[PDB]
Every structure is written in C-alpha cells, then in structure tokens.
Amino acid sequence: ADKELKFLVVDDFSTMRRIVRNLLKELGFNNVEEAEDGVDALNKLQAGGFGFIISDWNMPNMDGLELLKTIRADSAMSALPVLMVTAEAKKENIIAAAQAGASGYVVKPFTAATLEEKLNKIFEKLGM
Ligand SMILES: [Mg+2]
Image (tube, rainbow, N blue to C red; front, side, top):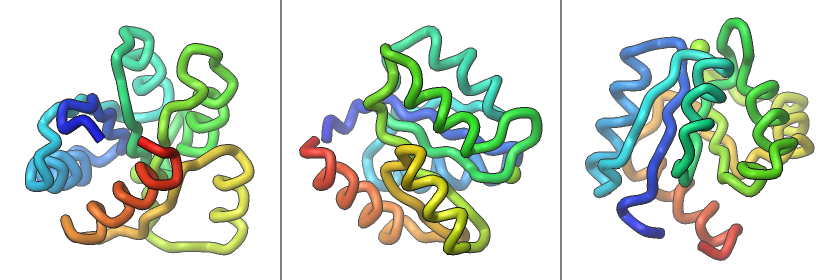
C-alpha cells in the first residue's frame, strides 16, 4: 500500500472524522479528505484520485450501506476498498454489507493497532 493513498473519511460526526484522520496519520497515511454523509462523499469522489474509503454505517440522507451500493455500481469507482465503521456489530448488518461489497467492518472505538490490522487484512485480501 502506497503511503500516499488518498483516503476519504465519511462520518456525520466531526470529532469521529478527526479521530480517524489522527489514527491514519499515526500509521503514516497523511492523504485524507472528509465528508459528512453519503451524498457529500459521492460529490467529493467525483473529483477523483481517491484510493480507500472509510465510511460510517449510520449517517443521515445517504447511509453507509447506500453509499457502498452506489460506489459498487459506478464503473469508475467499483473496485475502491470500503471499510465500514459501526458502534455495534450486528450479524445482519455485517451480512448486508458483505453482500453489497464492503471490504471489511470495524467496531468503534478502535485504536491505531486495530485500524492497522484491518487495513493490512484488506490490502492482503485485495492483493494491494
Ligand atoms: Mg454517524
């Protein structure tokens, strides 16, 4: 994984975005942009050059599942890695995301070490 991979962090909580950005920083990933909800994220993804999306499951207007399905359906972004974030792991949520193409799932709060492990797992799973 290129340390310069461009990340999109999506969460309706500013503070949760700041945590994720700070965690990534710690790992050496400084290339991060932020979005507030699914539609905000799609707007930004339009400009191109993103490499990895970290999205919250629970967001207004367009939730994580919807954003993920829209990414998967788009010819230009369909392969982008998507890491889903939830405050509470639920079997049907996990199955629904997997089936929709999520690259992985992480329960918050999480440390830099957990994030790293999730990141490496996906890079490994996707041969990146
Ligand atoms: Mg949220």
